[PDB]
Length: 138
Ligand SMILES: Cc1cc2nc3c(=O)[nH]c(=O)nc-3n(C[C@H](O)[C@H](O)[C@H](O)COP(=O)(O)O)c2cc1C
Image (cartoon, rainbow, N blue to C red; front, side):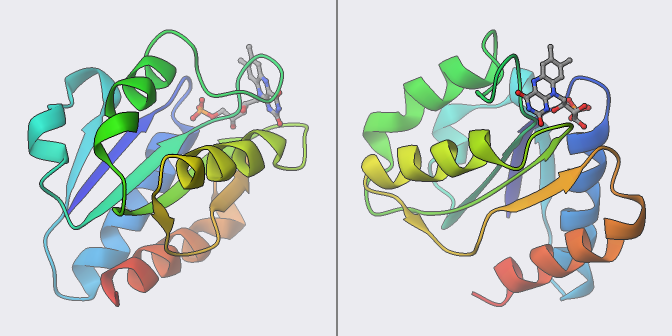
C-alpha cells in the first residue's frame, strides 16, 4: 500500500509511520511517501489512497505542496477508496471535516472516519497503529 503526507514539524510524519506500522503488523507492505517525492501515476494505481496533512494557516490544507497535489489528482480519483489523517494544534478538526467533504465531492469513497491527533501522537500512538489496521482490513 502507499501513504502520502505533508508534515511541517514531524507530527503528521510520525502518524504516517505509525499507520504504516499497523498495516505491516497486519501482514501487508506499505510505502510512506512525503508529498514532495510522490509520483501521481504510481499513486493512482493503488486500491486505497492514504493521505495526511496537518492543519495549516486557518483550518486549511498546506498550501505550497499538499493543496496542489490534491488539486492535481482530484479529477482522476472518482470511485477510489481514500483514508484521511493529520495532526492539528488548537482547533477541533475543521480542516479535516472540509478535507473529507472535498474528497467526497471528487467522487472518492472515504473508507474510515478521518484520523486526527493533536500535536505529536504520544498517548495516541496506538490509535494511529489501529487506524492502519482498519485500512489493512479493507
Ligand atoms: C502556520 C500554522 C498554522 C496552523 N493552523 C492551524 C489551524 O488552523 N488549526 C489547528 O488546529 N492547528 C493549526 N496549526 C497547528 C499544526 O496543525 C500542529 O502544530 C500540528 O501538530 C503540526 O503537524 P506537522 O508537524 O505534521 O505539520 C498550524 C500550525 C502552523 C505552523
